[PDB]
Image 1 (tube, rainbow over the protein chains, first blue to last red):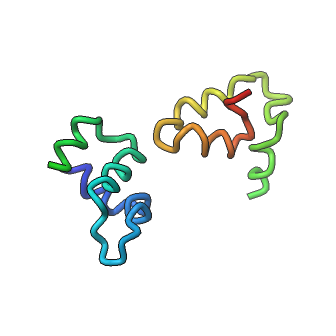
Image 2 (tube, rainbow over the protein chains, first blue to last red):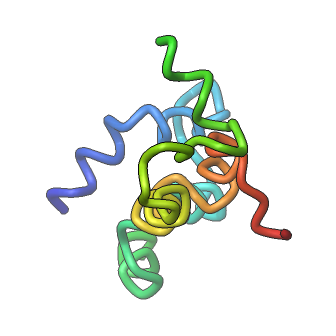
Length: 49
Length: 48
């Protein structure tokens, strides 16, 4: 939950956000985390949960 | 800014004896930027 704030600030995440309102998709958030290759699979699952 | 020209060049290390630079950099930064962005920047073909 410390790295989360960083990635949310990271433009890569803001880019992966296409929705104008800002809310990325559950499948799309999975992509943002996939890009940074920072959080591991189960970690991304927990973040989604 | 000028150096941005030799990165994709096939002979980037012509005088420097380290001929593994392109690979070293690719593998070290590859996970974060992917293996295709680094390959494009360094003009190296993974398919090759």
